[PDB]
Amino acid sequence: QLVPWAAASEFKETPELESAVRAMEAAANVDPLFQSALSVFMWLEENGIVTDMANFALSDPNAHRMRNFLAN
Amino acid sequence: SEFKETPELESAVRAMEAAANVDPLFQSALSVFMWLEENGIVTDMANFALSDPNAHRMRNFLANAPQ
Image (cartoon, rainbow over all chains, first blue to last red):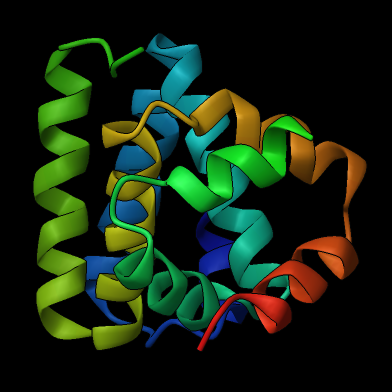
């Protein structure tokens, strides 16, 4: 289901990537919170902000600044 | 809120960790993924993404975050 998305993504095309995306879809099927996180995960990659967000999270380890941004 | 502790979760975490060990970019994505859940902002970020589908507003926030 998500293998074509993985193959076209910026992630390095490895057998581990392909098992990961499959496994994530299966986790999302049985847990809607994991599905919400998967949706964000894909949105970060599609918009090219994976490393930008990872770098931000280092500066905001408790999500304090992000949580206030999202709340407003 | 927290991920439901299903067998699928444990399988997904281990798969993601194995993909992250091979590819630093996937490790960055995994770190963000875990950071969202640890801090309880998964649904908040998912709702924001629905309203900012091209990440334009998120890009501006990240660009203006303190150095």
